Image (cartoon, coloured by chain):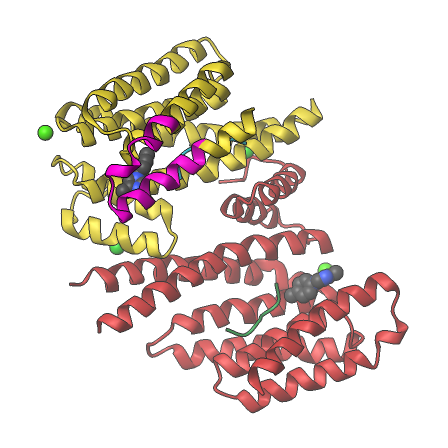
Chain colours: A green, B cyan, C yellow, D red
Amino acid sequence: RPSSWR
Amino acid sequence: RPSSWR
Amino acid sequence: AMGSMERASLIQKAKLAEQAERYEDMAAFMKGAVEKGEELSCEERNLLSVAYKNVVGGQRAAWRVLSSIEQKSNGPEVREYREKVETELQGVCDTVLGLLDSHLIKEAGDAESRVFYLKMKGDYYRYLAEVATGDDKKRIIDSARSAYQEAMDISKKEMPPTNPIRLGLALNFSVFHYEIANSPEEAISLAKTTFDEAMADLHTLSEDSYKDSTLIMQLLRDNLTLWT
Amino acid sequence: AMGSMERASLIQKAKLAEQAERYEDMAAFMKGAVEKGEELSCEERNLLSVAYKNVVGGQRAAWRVLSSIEQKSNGPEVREYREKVETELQGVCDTVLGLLDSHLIKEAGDAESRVFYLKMKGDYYRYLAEVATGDDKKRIIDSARSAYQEAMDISKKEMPPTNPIRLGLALNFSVFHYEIANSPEEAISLAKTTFDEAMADLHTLSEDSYKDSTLIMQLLRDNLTLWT
Ligand SMILES: *Cc1ccc(-n2cnc(C)c2)cc1
Ligand SMILES: *Cc1ccc(-n2cnc(C)c2)cc1
Ligand SMILES: [Ca+2]
Ligand SMILES: [Ca+2]
Ligand SMILES: [Cl-]
Ligand SMILES: [Cl-]
């Protein structure tokens, strides 16, 4: 659910 | 560009 | 590679692969199921079609990107990589056509199954035609035409005008006429005639069948709007 | 398999594969480029990272779909297919980690390159940790932690607080803390401290660098909003 780098 | 079945 | 897995397990895993959007796996599972030698149910035919349509669809999209880059350029890398993707696409088409020829079509006696497989055969020859440029381009186009035509003849004799397979077949045959055969007037005539006769048969349908049929009639209308 | 292709041709084809959204091909091309034995430029490191992040990203998404189906169920098919996807994911992670260990990291002397590769090492051990359940789960987690920690130490000594690699590293290390290490307070503290020190350094940046840095600070803020 949380954002890692993209 | 034109639609085939999908 | 799937010879040791149960037919039912291959079908179940094909459905799991669809949910996971793993269409390569899905196609491999359905190829294994076909190679068990038993005829396919309606649901199983749809799984086979969805799997390979998604696989070849990604290859066709990639080929079009690379072909566009190649045209704007004309080192060998762009051509080489376009050729690589093109060869992989042709291999998938050959695999599907091989499954239809060995032995799905010859065992398909019912109109729903036979028209479904012949539509598939027309579609995958159409995909071969999209990338073909050599001495066999005309024969590939005529193989698509012949498969679509036999499917059309059966569908008009054996199915109502609102049948979703009949409608999708006519949609794709009209796209064949417009994009492959350089016959835009034939494409428009087929799409309009198909739409109008379906319209006139909608009154016979349940609410669910009505939704199925009108969904595909909308695609016919979208093309007519694009083409006229 | 790429040993016979020129390094420059592999790089050019990796860029073509990205445009075609053929990330498996992209990763194979960049693997071949790495195996030429020369260090990677900034742009080339980004190509390597983008390729494998997209490949493993699709595997992780599929694994999560299948794992969810498996939990709701608990025949062997769901477990078998989840295990198949999981094994393929672990193979990709092992391949990336093998490239970092042979010999990208040991030849990376500059802060930008060394932090980049150590962040990658933490990321792919994190992906292994997401599916790990056996006797090596703790060691896999500590391998991720150790790689992230060394990257953090170098980045805090050698890069400004707005450096995009430093920011993305802190973002991912905070996700590691929250999702893998069961340390949500550490995750929140790292994200807030990283965001605040970046905020205070934005005044030194050009318009283009400001856009690069604020883009990643927004991801830190999104997580903080999710977590608090
Ligand atoms: C080629 C083709 C056309 C239409 C269908 N379809 C859509 N909805 C149903 C019940 C069948 C499948 C394949
Ligand atoms: C892991 C990571 C973080 C940030 C970048 N990035 C974004 N924009 C630039 C110039 C660098 C790449 C990779
Ligand atoms: Ca039969
Ligand atoms: Ca060096
Ligand atoms: Cl190639
Ligand atoms: Cl499996």
Residue interval drawn in magenta: C196-220
Q: Residue C215 magenta-drawn?
A: yes
Left of C52 or right of it: where is A2?
Answer: right
Please give the name of the residue rendered at 25% of the width and 53% of the height, measured from the top-left corner: C13
Left of D17 or right of it: where is C26?
Answer: left
Secondary structure mainly formed by the magenta segment: helix
Rendered location of residue D67, percent (x, y): 33, 68
Left of D66 or right of it: where is D5?
Answer: right
On the question of residue D111 being in view, the answer is no
Please give the name of the residue rendered at 38% of the width and 77% of the height, measured from the top-left corner: D136
Nearest to the observer: residue D125 or residue C114: C114
Nearest to the observer: residue C189 or residue D192: C189
Q: Ligand 3: which quarter? A: top left
Please give the name of the residue rendered at 29% of the width and 67% of the height, measured from the top-left corner: D69
Left of D62 or right of it: where is C205?
Answer: left
Query: Residue B4, relative to residue D73: is it above or below?
Result: above
Rendered location of residue C206, percent (x, y): 24, 45
Query: Residue C89, relative to residue C10: is it above or below?
Result: above
On the question of residue C141 being in view, the answer is yes
Nearest to the observer: residue C15 or residue D139: C15
Asked which quadrant contains residue C89, the reply is top left
Rendered location of residue C40, percent (x, y): 17, 38
Please give the name of the residue rendered at 33% of the width and 45% of the height, measured from the top-left corner: C211
Nearest to the observer: residue C157 or residue D140: C157
